[PDB]
Length: 169
Length: 170
Ligand SMILES: Nc1cccc(Oc2ccccn2)c1
Ligand SMILES: Nc1cccc(Oc2ccccn2)c1
Image: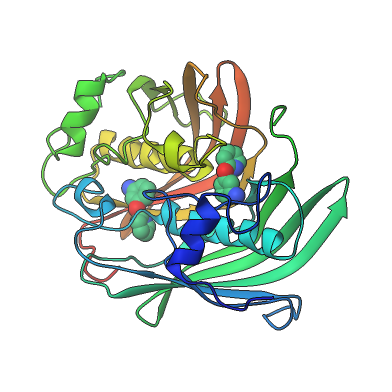
């Protein structure tokens, strides 16, 4: 129904209060790497099968700058990659599928730039490639990560699944 | 290139730029550091005969990322185990005596087919160096696996990390 989500919406999601008990959650701080979803739809995007656009505000005091690395601060590439997986899980919940998310992996990932503590904003762009409903539900997507209008990462074939039991995962 | 195992204190020393020295490869500090010890590192053996690292992370229920990922469904973020793999490829290149600071360059293919729960005892990382490249800058390609208490749970083909004597342009 809704086509954008605020940070307070995402934080509701992290407690289970957006999609409800048993269903997709985002991480809470300090693993949450999205502040807002500025667009989400089941049409458009590079495959015409859905799209998400989300943002993370950067400032110099975010926790990961101090420890990664000392004397050389740079946002962990893995955390920007995670934001993309978490967004694909969110999409699956947003579509109304039951169950909890687990990332299943990726085809090619490329890092070819960085997020410094002087950056203002990271943007994630997700293009849903295919949704699969075979015993369990999953999605395949391509994503990019940009910082202040410059593309810095790409991932082809992000996969995320929903699990109504993770006991055996 | 003569020490073949590293303690947690060696790895914290690396995180401060004090193992390989200033301007050279570092590991993250807590709470981004995802390795407790390197039990084996060599420039021979491994699946390609071109080098190997075996590292460990001890798991207990109080590790920070369990409480926030996720509420009511605690599970070690896959991205952090994947990062460990990249940081170990970085360390390899530092350990080989190359100058410069690490940036991961990506991966060919990543698979998660299990999980680390807060009841787990130990994660092991196995890194098989495939190729080192010296073309103006230096980088390494490697395959890797993440296991928990004996069970393989993640793989990554074609991990790439480079060393950058100037990250300004990156
Ligand atoms: N929804 C979502 C997205 C990314 C990571 C994830 O957690 C994990 C953790 C371990 C194995 C696989 N996925 C869940
Ligand atoms: N040495 C090393 C290993 C893993 C990640 C990394 O950081 C990043 C951060 C942004 C872009 C690329 N690499 C550095």
